[PDB]
Image 1 (spheres, rainbow over the protein chains, first blue to last red):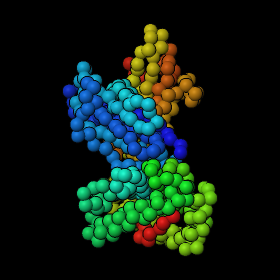
Image 2 (image 1 turned 90 degrees about the horizontal axis):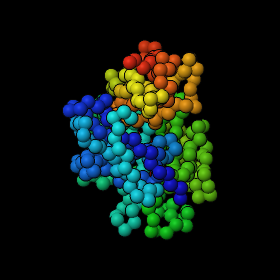
Image 3 (image 1 turned 120 degrees about the horizontal axis):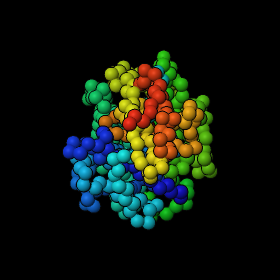
Image 4 (image 1 turned 180 degrees about the vertical axis):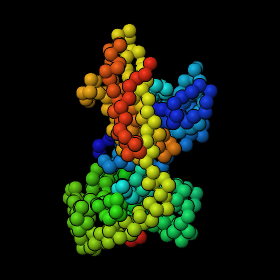
Length: 100
Length: 276
Length: 9
């Protein structure tokens, strides 16, 4: 069976302003099979109560999901998304960069 | 404007860990409006857009019956597909089905769709004629024979030309405040030094609906397709979408580069530059 | 709204 590794973007709902509440998003897409493990991290620890969209898929049958949580960005705090999937030998961490 | 309705369905088996998980969602255009998850406590189809909430109890009861029925048929189909592909009972497998309809500005059927995939690969699709089938392999040809014998395509044609279009039109009316509103991108250009000699110009498009957009960079009015980094369009989480396009530019040459934005919501296409 | 009739492969 053919497998497809997820694309991953980590980003905020609104342009980040330090001290102002916002949403942190991790969008995983283009993957198969559908089981996937996604964490949002604040200084390397799992953020609790992250929500996610219901499983859906694109024209080419590959899957996509949005994981999100409320967050307040600061100068110092480091945010990231950790993704694991059968196509990955180890979990992939993508750092949040407010300029991307 | 033209519009679409789609129902998406996924079952994933989990041998030794109970029955398959079934998730189905419905969309009008790029708007999610209904969902059902078989693992929820006493599962019901639930609304996900304000304009569907007004449908009465009988609507939700019938939807829930169909969703529960589809979970059952998907369980059966996953067992059948193991046989068709001589597969053991040990592995997880995936069954997907999509169907729905496209309509033009005047509400007429443009195209109907009904297709299945197994383990991420095309399985069987209803053709555009809504009368004949495309089977991907000899297993799907078994299904094709069964569905031809039962005149399934005729059933689907009737649904797709009829109820699919009629209910899509009803939803477009009831949801006219949102479904028939295109929100233009809010745009700006940022500047990111790489060295003393070059920097990245990033052209942002935020808060737009629907997802369709065109974002390009030009240099002296000439397209820079090969040297533009373009990220995949991504959901903001509030119904809207985001995208950006970036080019690497020599220091001081920034005014020669223009970002061009086309979107249904814009009064006119935009031309933007970095503004120090 | 969804199609009512069932279908199996």
